[PDB]
Amino acid sequence: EIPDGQITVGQRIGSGSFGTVYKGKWHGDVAVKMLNVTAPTPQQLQAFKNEVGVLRKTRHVNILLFMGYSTKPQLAIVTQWCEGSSLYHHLHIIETKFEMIKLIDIARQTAQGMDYLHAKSIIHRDLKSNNIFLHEDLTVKIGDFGLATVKSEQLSGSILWMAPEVIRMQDKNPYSFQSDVYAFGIVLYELMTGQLPYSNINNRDQIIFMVGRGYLSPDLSKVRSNCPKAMKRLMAECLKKKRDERPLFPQILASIELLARSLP
Amino acid sequence: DEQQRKRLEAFLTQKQKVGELKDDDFEKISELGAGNGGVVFKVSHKPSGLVMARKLIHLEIKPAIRNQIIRELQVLHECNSPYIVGFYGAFYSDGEISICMEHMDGGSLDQVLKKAGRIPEQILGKVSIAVIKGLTYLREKHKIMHRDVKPSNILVNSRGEIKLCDFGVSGQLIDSMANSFVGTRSYMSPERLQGTHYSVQSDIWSMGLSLVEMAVGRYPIPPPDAKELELMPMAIFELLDYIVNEPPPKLPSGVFSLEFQDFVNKCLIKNPAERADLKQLMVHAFIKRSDAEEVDFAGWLCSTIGLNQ
Ligand SMILES: Nc1ncnc2c1ncn2[C@@H]1O[C@H](COP(=O)(O)OP(=O)(O)CP(=O)(O)O)[C@@H](O)[C@H]1O
Ligand SMILES: Nc1ncnc2c1ncn2[C@@H]1O[C@H](COP(=O)(O)OP(=O)(O)CP(=O)(O)O)[C@@H](O)[C@H]1O
Ligand SMILES: [Mg+2]
Ligand SMILES: [Mg+2]
View 1 (cartoon, chains in turn red, cyan):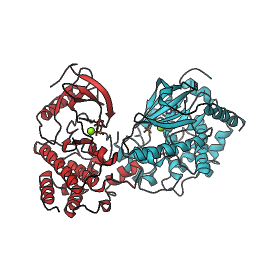
View 2 (tube, chains in turn blue, brown; view 1 turned 90 degrees about the vertical axis):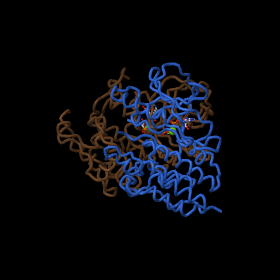
View 3 (cartoon, rainbow over the protein chains, first blue to last red; view 1 turned 120 degrees about the vertical axis):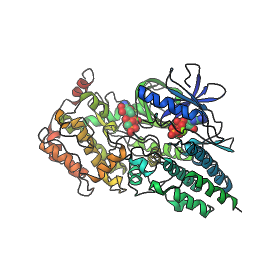
View 4 (spheres, rainbow over the protein chains, first blue to last red; view 1 turned 180 degrees about the vertical axis):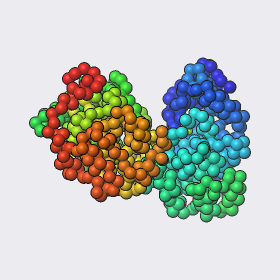
């Protein structure tokens, strides 16, 4: 489970909400990520060991496999490189124009991966379009899932995909299956508007406070005109402020597939 | 004043000799610190020989929007003032936006505050004057707000100078920064948090909240317990709900001037309309009390870090 200096490290790629990733060499094309958390209390390290254990086993075609963790150079995690661009890059940097069937498809495969993860009782906890890659522009690979111990509670990264209860940080643990379902709804918002939520608000603390207290939610009028009605209803169901009202991925997958059948 | 005209001009001349900024022309000297999204380095510009500070922002954004940001930062070339950090240039290269500004060997008041424990009211007087004068210059002559007033945004140097930096000249930059990089605390007015735009009122609140903190050496939301006030956390949603729902911070009873307590109180009232304005603060009694005073701010700063000047 724990490698020891065997690994090679390469070009700096960039840094996210809980680590810095570089292209590496644990074998052909691995992707290694030095975690922000670096002084692990032994109580924290134990939970990390067991979480990596649960993560080693996860194999699914819409999921990027997690290979191991190295502590000795620096506490790092190691995962497969992904030649494709992330979904955030396609939508929001290069503005890839897709047609509705492929957007629905991307939604479907994401839902397949999330349903596999919830089937194995893994809360993603960091679902963003930043963490969905389009492999060779065809398959979907979800990454950066699990690892609850490394993310410590303070928020970090982008607020945009966090549910109200995640933003409040008032429950024992606010992250649940339905938190993932909320994040996934923001990703559906992304797919169906080509746009991030709250494009009209440039005050980050305003967004945090107002979606925290249920005063602000995505503007669903900005969904594009060829968006199926069923898809828009599903989006709205995923984004309910109260977590108990959101659906679980088994019925989300059902919904999306039965939707995708009845297309032109 | 005589001396602002002198020093400002000198900056403009050795800015005239800088020319066009290119990445290969900078050598890294040392690290000045990092924020939520930016990193700052003390660098040497070889063709001119100047030493400056280079902020580097790494954003994942449409190239159209990045070129918009660069165009809008170009406005900094005309925001020249003794209360505004000197600006040399801004450009894009190797995935990074670079903002080149004059180096301030005092650093920010955020760090100074860590090194001094508390900052005396005497010194906060001169600081308040510098910030009010800067916000005023921004508003009167460029119709632009700061939008991010806080001690990490107030820079000082060993020549006694106090200057503002990181003010909102590029809205695209703000809205980019908004889509990532959560922080852990906030200096955001209660009117802005609820989506109200009452202009320059937002920056006055922020300054007030700054003052309290540097006066006591603690970010004042929430107020300290009676046992922790003796010595003279919250996730960010709780902080914001506290700023919105509960009454504003306050200075301690006797340890501070009555005029200073009144100044911060008028800065911190939660109604943006009855809160003090720039022209009112400018003539507040603590402000005149402090402008009459003759302090050795350069020497005080140096004593708080290093050698006297
Ligand atoms: N297995 C992987 N393969 C290729 N690139 C990866 C990768 N994992 C991360 N990256 C890329 O490295 C850069 C930073 O990684 P990181 O995941 O930390 O940022 P991020 O935008 O995904 C926010 P988060 O930390 O919440 O996942 C990103 O550009 C990301 O797309
Ligand atoms: N012209 C300048 N001269 C000297 N030091 C500077 C400087 N500009 C910035 N710095 C230093 O870099 C540090 C970090 O700068 P930056 O503005 O990116 O983050 P910040 O400290 O303002 C917190 P945030 O990112 O939340 O706004 C500042 O505290 C300051 O000490
Ligand atoms: Mg990621
Ligand atoms: Mg700053």
